[PDB]
Image (cartoon, rainbow, N blue to C red):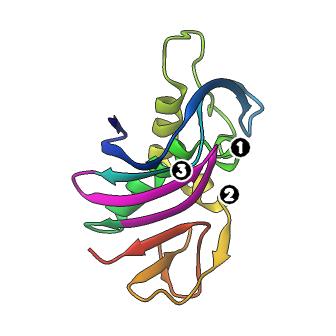
Amino acid sequence: SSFSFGGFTFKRTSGSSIKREEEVLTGNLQTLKIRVHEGYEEFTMVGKRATAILRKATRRLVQLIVSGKDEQSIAEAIIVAMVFSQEDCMIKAVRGDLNFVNRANQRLNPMHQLLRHFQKDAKVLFQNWGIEHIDNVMGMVGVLPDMTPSTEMSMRGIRVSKM
């Protein structure tokens, strides 16, 4: 069960899931209908300039270990992972003027509209994701919302591995 999303090939390595169509509110209090995968799953994300191991529970990213060509390649894989996770803080980061999803055509994908939104500017996404203190794990570094490597702090659940 290998699928494609945001230029990444996802491949499930553990867990299972059932789908539930659900309604969610953005930071602009706009209702989106999304197809939610319920169940704890693990995936490999393989792209041309980045790779990752993604561990996730229903609408919640548990951990993401990213490896890539450079900061831009890695941020790109982080954005895809955060949108794919379907986390409330990612949905609530959709806010402000013009930041609305065209839902007049119900066949269109709100996940692809969330992705386009965060690909343009992930600043609100990364700042609203939350940060956390990080453990020892040498060879794995933390990454701040501005993509600065840190040994003391990181975006919640996100770690950068050496390529």
- Secondary structure beneath dot 3 equals helix
Q: Disc number at residue 128? A: 2
Q: Is residue 84 located in the magenta-colored stretch of the structure?
A: no
Q: CA distance from mark 1 to mark 3?
A: 12 Å
Main secondary structure found in the magenta portion: strand
On screen, residue 119 versus residue 104, left or right, reads left
In the foreground, 11 or 79:
11
155 versus 114 height, above or below: below
Mark 3 to mark 2 CA distance (whole Å): 11 Å
Q: Secondary structure at mark 1?
A: helix
Q: Total marks drawn?
A: 3
Q: Residue at x 64, y 44 (%)?
A: 59
- The residue pinned by badge 3 equals 82
Q: Nearer the viewer, residue 101 or 135?
A: 135
Q: Amino acid at mark 2?
A: Asn
Q: Identify the residue position indicated by label 1 in the image.
A: 92
